[PDB]
Length: 478
Ligand code: NI
Ligand code: NI
Image (cartoon, rainbow, N blue to C red):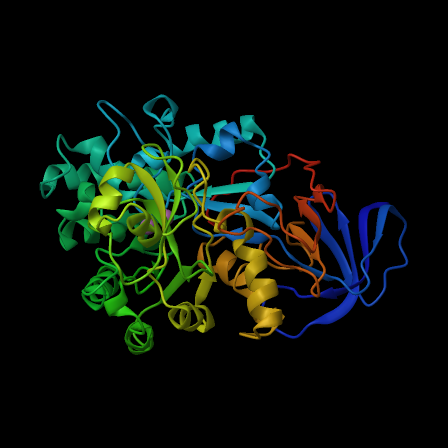
């Protein structure tokens, strides 16, 4: 009878995108018990949340935390932002159902070394999450490139009918055990030689609401309308939902072309169900590539094993200090990590203002000197873009990382502050919330986040310390 938590006088932004209101919210166990203008109830712990916003736990729909949630259960980078659930297994790479008979193909090395791929079924990955006891919930997609490596000798050829038939059966068993859908990373060499027909066969397993098709497009540059026209056809072939992962118009030539892609979205969202996600930044973070070296935008060096002295400077500054060309300056700096300012700020804002666009950090945890999105992708939307820049009301901003995300991936009883739903909550100050992570100082906790609750367990406070490990493995709504 005595509730566990009572949030008094909080501005409730329920994550539905609807109007905000002030009320009391009571939690008993892992469920939201009561919501009323006031609650004269006895509680074990009470919090006066006046002037604060009580919102659903933030859902990071685009992560690569397949292995990291297990060896770092207290996932401070996401929890300090207010993330209570991560969707892993994006871009065709996933640790679930992955089997390694030889070497690790690209880009599955982002998840971890061979030694960590020990999850041949979704059930085996689920129990490993439960054993690790993480601080946040974990749901997984199935990586197409991982399914290829389980059934093909070489990944640089079109798959035969027998190999594709085996992938459909393994994907079917994964979806029955709680997988959220299928992810593809077609731009990578391990899946570039795949026909659209092969992806169509796998996407058919997602019919009748058995998953969502998230896609790293085959090209995010000039032929992006081609790759989008693909992506929509595979969804139209099996009548399955499509989510364009980290939608961006990379390359100086494609700057401003979001007016063309989002228009292609509008025309095709009148025939099928389409969505997308993106991180609120106009700069990339990857390895220093010779084919990516250019003068059209800044290329800041994060780390450089060859020349560790030249760090934090643009490639043009390094090339001028050495009095050598750009391609030769990079050649002597490689291998290195670089920040590619290859995106236009107006393009990011258009994608963010798009109604069916979700917020995905796409953070790289194992990456030494990581992109600041790993520590402040979600507070950046709530603070800089919603409050300061006024891109959208705070209700819409919260909706793009909660209810819209939970409904898209069919997360049962999550993403909403509602009676009977799970008690994944975050209490933040709407006037001071901001991303503190910068490109020079990325691994830094955010401000304004005052409380984070996972399944009714208070897991993170304003002292920047993790106090709970009540994360669970989430299975698709059945
Ligand atoms: Ni990707
Ligand atoms: Ni990704």
